[PDB]
Image (cartoon, coloured by chain):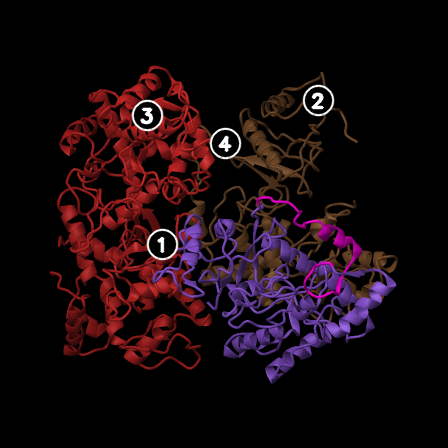
Chain colours: A purple, B brown, C red
Amino acid sequence: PQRVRDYQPAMLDELLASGEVMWSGAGQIGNGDGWVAFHLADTAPLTLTHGAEIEFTDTHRVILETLGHGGAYFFRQLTDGTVEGTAGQELKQALWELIWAGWVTGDTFAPVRAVLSGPRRGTDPTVSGRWSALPAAEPDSTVRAHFQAELLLGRHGVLTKGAVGAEGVPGGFATLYKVLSAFEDAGRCQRGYFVESLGGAQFAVASTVDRLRSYLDNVDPERPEYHAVVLAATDPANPYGAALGWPTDSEAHRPGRKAGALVALVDGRLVWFLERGGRSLLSFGADADAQRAAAGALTDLVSAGRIPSLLVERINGVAVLDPDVDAERAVVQDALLGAGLSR
Amino acid sequence: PQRVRDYQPAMLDELLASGEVMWSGAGQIGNGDGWVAFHLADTAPLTLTHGAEIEFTDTHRVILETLGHGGAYFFRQLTDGTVEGTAGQELKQALWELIWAGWVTGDTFAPVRAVLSGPRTDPTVSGRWSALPAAEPDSTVRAHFQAELLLGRHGVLTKGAVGAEGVPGGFATLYKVLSAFEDAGRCQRGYFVESLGGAQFAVASTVDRLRSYLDNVDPERPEYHAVVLAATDPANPYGAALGWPTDSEAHRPGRKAGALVALVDGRLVWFLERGGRSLLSFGADADAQRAAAGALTDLVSAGRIPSLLVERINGVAVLDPDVDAERAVVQDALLGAGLSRTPRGLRL
Amino acid sequence: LDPAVVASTSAQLQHLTPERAARDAEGVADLLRLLGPLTEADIAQRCTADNIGAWLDGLHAAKRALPVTYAGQTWWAAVEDIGLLRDGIGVPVPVGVPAAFTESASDPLGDLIGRYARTRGPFTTEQTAARFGLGVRVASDVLSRMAVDGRLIRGEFDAQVLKILRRRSLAALRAQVEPVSTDAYARFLPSWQHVGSTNTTGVDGLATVIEQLAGVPIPASAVESLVFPQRVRDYQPAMLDELLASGEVMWSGAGQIGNGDGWVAFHLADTAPLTLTHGAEIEFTDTHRVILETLGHGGAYFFRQLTDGTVEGTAGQELKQALWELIWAGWVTGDTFAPVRAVLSGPRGTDPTVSGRWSALPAAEPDSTVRAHFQAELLLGRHGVLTKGAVGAEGVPGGFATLYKVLSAFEDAGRCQRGYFVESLGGAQFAVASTVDRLRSYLDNVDPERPEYHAVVLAATDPANPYGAALGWPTDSEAHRPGRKAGALVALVDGRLVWFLERGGRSLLSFGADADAQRAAAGALTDLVSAGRIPSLLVERINGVAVLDPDVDAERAVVQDALLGAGLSRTPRGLR
């Protein structure tokens, strides 16, 4: 809802149920939430993963037999054993263990809205939509490499040694660079020294670099714009962590790139950081009311209802709020109080 | 959207996919209009009907025999290596003919929302299409469930409503089974509505609710509540239990699809036919037409119905100098409600 | 205990009246469930159509309401009680039963006699032993232990039945119908002011809610947050501001709050100089004098037009502090409700909190008979039955001793009918006639049933909250005593006032500690939080009086468990 700008959860279920995209969960946080990775129907076997190598117990073995031969099935008909009773309730745990593994997917995206709500005639929603086997991901070949390269060049503006490290392609940058240079030799891409760091091998399609050639700070003295944007740390749009390391300033404590960690960043400089909600803050750099724009952004979020918490913000990286207030820390709580009570 | 005060269509597809209801259309009309019959999923085999009979060409058999021993599929996985170019148009036309007979069922209400949108990946066949569970064979259980369901739907089950409703064995078989109910005691067995003049079984509790609405013995000005209804939704007693007023000796209205009966304070004042172009005032009374007109205008302005700019009556359609009294009141009513007059005689 | 009353009441409790009889095949099973097992020869006395011989077989075939042969002759009993009765006395249930609900996890004979007593009138200890096949003294053993619990008490030749028998007998002693319990009035007053009513919607519904809530001062913070949006089902703060802009209601301000949430008080425009309190009579400096000069002499003016020559500066902030206080007196109103929406926002080019046109309120009517007549009729409109109490909180000038005079002219001429309507209140209790018929509902009937537990949450200073105007506060605790205070929540399930939240989550009370009934108020308050109607989430710092994490209080043990049932978590409170 930060990019679409007009999002109703009934807009995703519509796209899902048509058969345009695939759900295809993979990974797990624990106690629900997990790690969902969308797809597209035409090119699903290309941009999918192999598997998870789960234990494959017998109650797992019965499911994959039914879903194996055909298309989508409901919960109540997944097997013959009655869903009534513990033998029925034990199934849903055996299934959601198969989901996060990435073998079966539900096409409605109602389930993974249930497991987010909480642990609290088939009234339960946690297994409601019809579940289906997932198409056998095409084995790595010459075509999967080409398509993945094009996809990466489309997702990132430029493709560096860093972002390939975060994306975790099989074979590392060493193998991908082979096909990247094959492109630029054939055309379809040009390799230049586009951003001064990150080494001297950055690939980009010649259209992007035009846009990127904008946004440069012109050679003039001028008051900065002080723009503000707030992203999840583990959001693709977040550079810090991919092709851009975390700031060397304030590093003895690792901010990291994990779930629920907001990253408020004024136009280019990483200013704040949140962790496991609105609890622990990290002020990497300090500036005069540049913190104010980030505070405005966080407050606009919590007001709009996008992020759940009310941002207590009780701990700083040194945990100095009430005792022995730091002068560099004071600006943080001050710029915050002008925005939000922090309570 | 009339009996669910707030209804956004995305509210329905939330049910269909969850697995609690089954749409199962079971009757075809013209082109781009059908008979859908929402069943519940717990007791679907009971309220379902046997599959219709059709030509059963070979491509139909291809659509089946795959949906048969399986749960459900997308449109593409029905057959293999057939694109929307030439075999698709034959496969699709084979599908929408297989569903109006009632053998397959969408996993959501998205396609039918399109097939009505008129000819203008394709939206016409999107969701998963499932083979449909065979209807429970007629037995004693089917009979009891249908009888109890009918009693739940209509207030006082009559000999009439069983007529318009399609039940095997006619009203003669129900009276045989409802007598078993009256013996056990789950039904009142009282002469509740007089003109029906039969045996209305009803229920113990409903009668207590039905005994209200009884006209008060003293004289009182009427309340004038106008409630427009589609001519064929079960909340329309006429044509099923009450029967139509005998007017227009030759020209007779019915329960046609797309017609509107606008009844105010119980009595029906008007009748629309096939989306405008015919108004069938039945013994009008002044200032009652005002209420029905207000009903129609709030309906069209809320958007639930495509506007009506085409108007006629029995034979006096538009600006007949032979103007009658009964045609007058209709005019004085429609102009007062603000409906436009003489935009054109026709419409292309 | 009038022998006449004790007859009918013991009759209609036993479902013996011609009205209130089973008319159905299932209305018979409801007999067997409400009161104890009884013989079919007896059931025939309850049901209307006496062809029972098939109704009872229908239940047997459907495997419900099985028959048993214990205690001499055989009589039927509900399946749910076949488990209890089995272990109590007689042969056990046949193995044909599903027996899912049969298995007992507690003492049978402690519950088979209880319902048998709660149903009938005053009864002898000799009869129960015959009905249940017991001896003689073995029965008196139970009646003894039953008296210690609070169920069985003496009734002259059944504690809950004695309450009813005393209530009806006395009410029969004088010639008057039995009054509804004060709990029933607490259920009645909200719905008499449209609380949670879906009939009311749109601006034509808000111009109804106002005319009834006219003249009563309520805090600006609660308006359009907890008092209007509860009764005007959909409420968008324009439809109020659009009303104000026309000549329909005159938003007036009375009282004063340090925070800035001034006691606003709405009035219709036809009847303003009646329901308008006079004024405040504060000292008048130069600025206050110059405002009243212009702002009163003509119709109205903008903000900038009040002063002259010097538009703004350090003089702008002082005059904005002069006017915006002159309004909290009641001498000047705003032409819309847009400024006050800003003052609640706080300090957070043009400047709000002086936006709209400003005007001089009309000269309230001098105290006379017309004002008193109108005020009495209005109070009869707002409260259901106005007692000598609620007039106290409304603070009409002259006190109840001045109202009883003119209110007697009404009852004499025949517009209202005094009586004794609510259980425990004054003897005056006036009421219009059409209301009293509605009040005859909400009358908890004599038979025992499972409570409804339908929670509603008000603001403590909301006119719908009866507690503090008509009903007295529960005297549960004397040290920490609550009252009608701004921004306080009163959550009440059936009129019981189960909670009292104060000043956000800062304080919580536990008046009616009931299992399974704290949860209803918890759920309602959580819905208020989720819908955003409450301005802020709840914090829940203290409970009772500052209960700390160790050393759980027994009376308190259930309140926290109920709070856990809803969204609120175990995060340390006010960690700071």
What residue sits right under mark 3 in the picture? Answer: C332
The three-letter amino acid code for the residue at tag 3 is: Val
Label 4 chain ID: B
Marks 2 and 1 sit apart, C-alpha to C-alpha, by: 56 Å
Q: Earlier in the sequence, mark 4 or mark 2?
A: 4
Residue C107, quarter of the rendered image: bottom left
Residue C3 percent location from the top left of the image: 14, 54
Mark 1 — residue? Answer: C454
Q: Secondary structure at mark 1?
A: loop
Relative vertical location of residue B232 with respect to residue A152 in this rendering, above or below = above
Cα gap from disc 2 to disc 3, whole angstroms: 55 Å
Q: Residues within 10 Å of mark 2 (few under 14, many from 20)?
A: few
Label of residue B224 in the image: 4
Magenta part of the protein: which range? A194-223
2 vs 3, front mark? 3
Residue C406: x percent and y percent?
Answer: 18, 27
Amino acid type indicated by mark 1: His
Q: Please report, as a chain letter, where disc 3 is located.
A: C
